[PDB]
Image: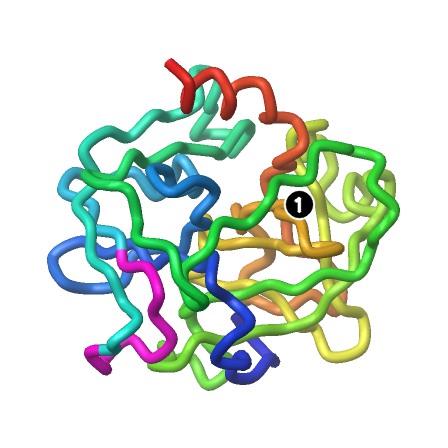
Amino acid sequence: LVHGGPCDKTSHPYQAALYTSGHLLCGGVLIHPLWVLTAAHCKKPNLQVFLGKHNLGQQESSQEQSSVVRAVIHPDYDAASHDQDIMLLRLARPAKLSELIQPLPLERDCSAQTTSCHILGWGKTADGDFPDTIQCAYIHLVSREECEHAYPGQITQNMLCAGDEKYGKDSCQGDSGGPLVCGDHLRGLVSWGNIPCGSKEKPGVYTNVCRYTNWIQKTIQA
């Protein structure tokens, strides 16, 4: 994510890192001890999940590594339009919760009143490089009409937009599937946005998590 800074060490216990072949691919959100939520476009064979991480290259006492044994892509995911960009990853074993590994509650109300939010991840920063330390930025939700105005014909009810008109704080490559946290609830997942990254003119686009409460619950309790 661009134009943010390193997160506080204790403030992101729900953040997951998704790796393949030993390297960061995407973010994700621990939403249940057995399940990480992420973007469908992050699906690859052999996904590995790291929980409790802050600095990627440090072996951290708080971290836990888990292979993904099942990846459940939303049945209505449309890769071409990015619509319904959501996926559930089942961990091989329940995560051992701690101060630094905790699930984040889902926002169930699509009409929720909190419009200022945090984004988090290890995606590309403003220097064009990938950070070792997880980054954070505060951004604000954009109305659907404003976002539709920015990406005509591309925004659906399954998408939420957010950005920062002052500095352009925005998610970027490698942040996909990570959290948009508003009012201490998971409101969105990083999905897509402008190229280059930066939200001064066009907002970032996030999967609208509130639309998926039923499907998430049904998948977890199957």
Which x, y percent locates residue 75?
Answer: 43, 16
Task: Name the foreground residue: 143 vs 67.
Answer: 67
Q: Residue at x 33, y 38 (%)?
A: 34
Q: Residue at x 18, y 53 (%)?
A: 20
Total numbered labels placed on residues in the image: 1
Task: Name the foreground residue: 32 vs 147.
Answer: 32
Q: Residue at x 24, y 60 (%)?
A: 64
Q: In which quarter of the image is residue 24?
A: bottom left
**Structure colour scheme:** rainbow
Regarding mark 1 in the picture, which secondary structure is present there? Answer: strand
Q: Is residue 5 magenta?
A: no
Looking at the image, is 38 positioned above or below residue 102?
Answer: above
Q: Is residue 202 left or right of residue 111?
A: left
Q: In this view, does 90 lie to the left or right of 141?
A: left
Q: Is residue 44 left or right of residue 144?
A: left
Q: Is residue 58 magenta?
A: yes
Q: Residue at x 38, y 80 (%)?
A: 131
Task: Name the foreground residue: 141 vs 118.
Answer: 118
Q: Give the range drawn in magenta.
A: 50-59
Main structural element of the magenta stretch: helix, strand or loop? loop
Give the amino acid at mark 1. Arg
Question: Which quadrant would the C terminus be assigned to in this image?
Answer: top left
- Crowding at dot 1, Cα within 10 Å, few <14 / some 14-19 / many 20+, comes out as many
Q: Quadrant of residue 54?
A: bottom left
Residue that numbered label 1 is attached to? 187
Q: Is residue 189 left or right of residue 205?
A: left
Which x, y percent locates residue 73?
Answer: 37, 26
Task: Name the foreground residue: 33 vs 181.
Answer: 33
Looking at the image, is 3 positioned above or below residue 124?
Answer: below
Looking at the image, is 44 positioned above or below residue 95?
Answer: above
